[PDB]
Amino acid sequence: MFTINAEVRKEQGKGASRRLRAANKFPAIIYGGKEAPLAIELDHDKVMNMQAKAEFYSEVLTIVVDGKEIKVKAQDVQRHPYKPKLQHIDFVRA
Amino acid sequence: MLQPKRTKFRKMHKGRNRGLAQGTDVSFGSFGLKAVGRGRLTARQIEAARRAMTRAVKRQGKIWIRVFPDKPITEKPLAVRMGKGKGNVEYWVALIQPGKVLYEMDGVPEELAREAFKLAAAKLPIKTTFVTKTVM
Amino acid sequence: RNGRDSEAKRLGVKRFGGESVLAGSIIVRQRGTKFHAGANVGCGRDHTLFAKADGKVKFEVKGPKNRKFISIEAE
RNA sequence: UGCCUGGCGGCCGUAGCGCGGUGGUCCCACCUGACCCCAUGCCGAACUCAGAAGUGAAACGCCGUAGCGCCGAUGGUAGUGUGGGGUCUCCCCAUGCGAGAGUAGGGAACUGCCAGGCAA
RNA sequence: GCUCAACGGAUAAAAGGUACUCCGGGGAUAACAGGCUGAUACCGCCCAAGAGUUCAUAUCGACGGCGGUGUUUGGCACCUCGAUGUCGGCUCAUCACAUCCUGGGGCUGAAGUAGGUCCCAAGGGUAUGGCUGUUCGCCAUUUAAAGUGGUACGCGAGCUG
RNA sequence: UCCUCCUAAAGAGUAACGGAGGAGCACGAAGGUUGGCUAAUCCUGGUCGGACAUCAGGAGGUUAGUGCAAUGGCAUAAGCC
RNA sequence: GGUUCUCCCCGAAAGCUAUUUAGGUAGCGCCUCGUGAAUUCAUCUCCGGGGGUAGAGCACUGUUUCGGCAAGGGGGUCACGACUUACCAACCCGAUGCAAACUGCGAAUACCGGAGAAUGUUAUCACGGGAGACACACGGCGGGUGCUAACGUCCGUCGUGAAGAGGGAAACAACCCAGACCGCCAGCUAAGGUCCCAAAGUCAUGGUUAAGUGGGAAACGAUGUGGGAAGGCCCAGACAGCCAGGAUGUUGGCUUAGAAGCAGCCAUCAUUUAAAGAAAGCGUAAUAGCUCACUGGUCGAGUCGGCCUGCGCGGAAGA
């Protein structure tokens, strides 16, 4: 039931991403296949709650962006160095 | 008293402790002590913390040390004027950046692990936190 | 027992890519051969690279070892 | 024009290694002999001369295979120029530049001139 | 033809003492005091292995950690070299409290007398002699106690030397 | 006094009684040219011989060597005959 | 040490090299006046450049932790054959780090060259006349040294002072704003400010703080208080209270000195069951004993333990 609400990022960069994280929202990327990579933004608190369990990285996940459903798998993720937070998530289209 | 063997040079520059820690994840055990603050740990402090946990766990499980001093520090003798060359090496310290995992541990219950790490952190000069091995 | 040093030899590139030079001008001063002589470039006994003809100096990478070469084109 | 072959290059690991297959009409290699030319700090090993019996074993060329090397995004991160701020032996904000490693993936080449054989 | 190596080489040719000292300068540069700093020192706290009949925390508390004071030993050379007399003693003091006594309390491995430790408290009080220039210290005998420090290591236009 | 590295902040230069080491030569060949050659370290077999002499094969591709400390360079070898 | 009238223009340095040289001096750098010269020079855009610094990495030179394979080494069964191992361990493989004197990678800036527009009193270069200066200081950034101490000391680069008044930081060369030709009882602003001293909001909206925090200080401690994300148990009725229960061998074999649950070898059994463990605290030489784990009944509705943090409290003693 791993449904993630995501939005398409408007601006990218170190300044934009840091500003985004300050608003309790972190970026992520979806790639794989012959489709262009898609940059997304999504809420941080919800992902932390549902990524705590060990099987979050086991099966496929569904990403809902602008009314479109994408099936992805957790490929890579970056933690905060010394805080319980997330910096980025890499998603591989399944 | 951790210390290197036959180091290339006896003395080295003071340097700086800027930057961010690299070994920020648990790699050997199931629980670890992460460094929140920034600073340096001497060999004596590392030994004191290690002894505290070994006693706390009562030689049960495994202990991993993820930091090595590998950095000499000098100190001028008392009543010595400035100059006349670099001071003699006294003790070895390890530079710690935020997020560095100091000690790792495995083979004990989570409850017993928390108190063991808490005792060790009480004998260290840097703010520390308890972390658990993450799945990927 | 320290305190000794040697006078700096002021090595390095004297003429950079894309600037005209006169024949015989020094292009690079080096201990070994970091750059190898190319076309219209000669190598001195101390591995100094000098221009054997008048023109524009350019750098390039050639050979199986990707070693750097300095050439001169008559422009 | 094509399959081939040899030489001289461009280009230089997407081009290099490992495993399997494939080639003797020419060419190439191995190969016989060496009294003479030539050489071994001893040896036809290597170099050189007189040959072409035999062979494709080795080497070399080509094909297949990702088992390695190699190349490699997007995003994020580190760092950083300029101007400001802070609980200022370290950081943050606005703007500009933006890695390294890693990931998806790519990948077991391409090309110019000359000469020779076969089919055209 | 020169370790003219003090290596741009003042002569071919050259070591010491001055508390009997002198002159020109310098706080550009030391010694006393101030200032900055706080390694060291002193004081307080954190963790707690252990000791304490068993019981870590009555009382001590190792291995380690974090602070305060500017009371020692230090670092620097900012002030003073057209001069700030620098150890003790005497006389006269004044302030801080990290309290020696007296006052009020908690805990005690506090039966009582007598203690141990911690908290609040600076109102007042807080020795005399022998030895030594001594501060200090040892010793003798008293007291409720003979407190610790700051004040140019208080005080020589107040005294002694 | 001179040489090499770091400090030195990716041109040059850049101080300290800062951190490490060297030189006051050598060579008529160790120079010039022509021709030829390509190491260290490991594995296996083999008298003395043994971990470590020399021989043969294999992996390796320069960890070797370069008259002298260090840095840079060196397969067209600047290395060896 | 001192060096005597006035006005106008420009305007430094405290660096390098050498010096019986270090507080002197010489050349150069920097200043001034004159002369002659090229879109000479500067900023910006674009283009052509070589770096090995920050960062990163561990192929190499060193260092470092763990696991495996493990040649080899010791003790042991063997009859010149040969074998095992509770035990030492090389080289490699997998993972994790570190380095000014490590680099299989590699910026931002800076620097050199070329083209172009605008702008600048030729701001550039060469030659000539005259100099001063060669004690620098603090601040930001990158470092060595020291204790990542010093208004310490030694370098690189920029700023200010020196040689710059004015406003601001209570006072305070070097901090922030800003470069004073003279006059005006004119206006608008910068940093910083607007209750009074003292010029200007007792201004507006939404929050926080109870501490005189604001208006010094840490490790660490705590039902201070605000917000956020969750999680367990909850009218088949939770949490705290209230009259209740908590027993039988397990005085154990074990080191029988007694540990019997309250020193440990040890299992961590088993019945009544609305319900109980062969045991968490206090207390005995051990006993005993008193509580809590857990379980009934009434009222009865929320309650409980952690994470993220905003602002506060203690820690906090000097003449």
Image: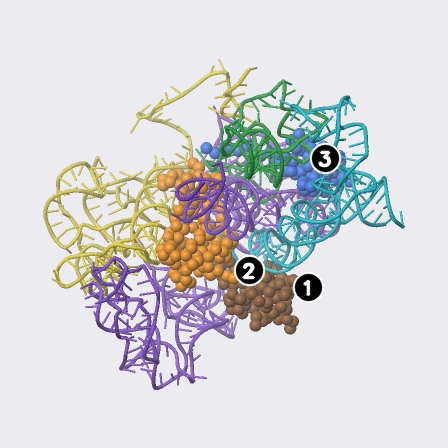
Chain colours: A brown, B orange, C blue, D cyan, E yellow, F green, G purple
Q: Which residue is drawn at 39% across and 61% down?
A: B112
- The chain to which mark 3 is attached is C
Question: Callout 2: few (<14), some (14-19), or many (20+) C-alpha neighbours within 10 Å?
Answer: few
Residue kind at label 2, given as amino acid type:
Gln
- Labels 2 and 1: the sequence-earlier one: 1
Query: Could you give the CA–CA distance between mark 2 and mark 1, rounded to whole angstroms?
Result: 23 Å
- The chain to which mark 1 is attached is A
Select label 2 or label 1 by which is in front: 1
| Residue closest to the eye, E30 or G37 | E30
Quick one: SS at disc 3?
Answer: strand
- Residue tagged 1: A35
Residue E52 is situated, as x and y percent measured from the top left of the image, at: 22, 56
- Residue tagged 3: C41
Question: Callout 1: few (<14), some (14-19), or many (20+) C-alpha neighbours within 10 Å?
Answer: few
Residue kind at label 3, given as amino acid type:
Val
Q: Which residue is drawn at 63% across and 69% down?
A: A70
Quick one: SS at disc 1?
Answer: loop
Q: In this view, does B92 lie above or below E54?
A: above
Q: In this view, does A65 lie above or below E73?
A: below
Query: Could you give the CA–CA distance between mark 2 and mark 3, rounded to whole angstroms?
Result: 52 Å
Q: Which mark is residue B72?
A: none
- Residue tagged 2: A78
Residue F69 is situated, as x and y percent measured from the top left of the image, at: 53, 32
Query: Could you give the CA–CA distance between mark 3 and mark 1, rounded to whole angstroms?
Result: 51 Å
Residues at discs 3 and 1 in contact (Cβ within 8 Å) = no
Q: Residue at x 53, y 69 (%)?
A: A50
Q: Is residue E113 above or below residue G135?
A: below
- The chain to which mark 2 is attached is A
